[PDB]
Length: 330
Image (cartoon, rainbow, N blue to C red; front, side):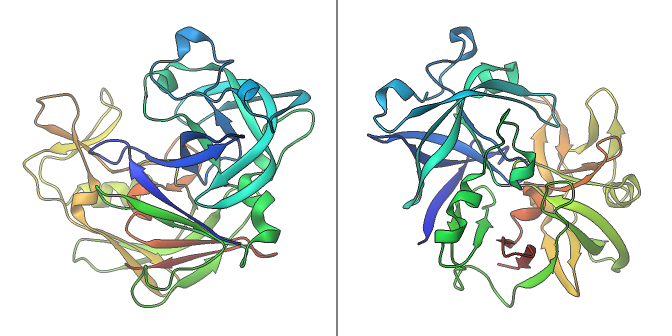
């Protein structure tokens, strides 16, 4: 089997991407944030504290003839940005772009933090990291990909995120029309539960390539590119007026600037992020200070190849017995 679904930016800055997901019988369609940096499929629901729901579409398990309470199971997750959610668990039928999993754990939120409530466009998350990170207790649950894997034509999914435009998640096949040149594959460590790999270096604009190993994760659920402070400083030094602002929470730059590109290495291959992908707009409405799309990972504890980086590539998440990652230009 295969599946293919369009993923759509939630706003004009590509702050996140939502992908429609069918849950239950009859189908209830929710727009979920596909997140290769976590492993829980959780949804706003009829059980979510009423004051914490503000415009999201909810899953109502009592209206699904295929929903079953997973008795005794609970979940609770906290993300890198300080946001969180928790609740109980149902199993139900879940379909993405024509690909159907029966008995998928659907984690129903009883509580969500303010960041989630305030974002009316995201109805929940669909985790695509390794199932070892799944938070369900006392019986850990499998991701949608893990459940689908054996049924797929090939044990892969691909992320093709757009810049200020829709893109595609495919399951079970590689669309050879969706990228240019060849796909370069690179090793993955699953030791921390992530799609963790080592970039071979970087360049800023038309500058020379610096060969240096940068360990990080391919994370569709993180908006920006988070890299070591040395790398980030080298990038922003090429932008007149750019500075790190503790009050804003990272690098800002004059909105009048033309940003240079940023290149990252994948083996001997190179992925070029155009300068415009690195502009996240005014820090507040009407400001002439703009937020940068490349930020320091210092204090995160891991480098993160988030959407800024991934949307410059066609990305293969290869879930073979020894997982790997593939990147192509597009």
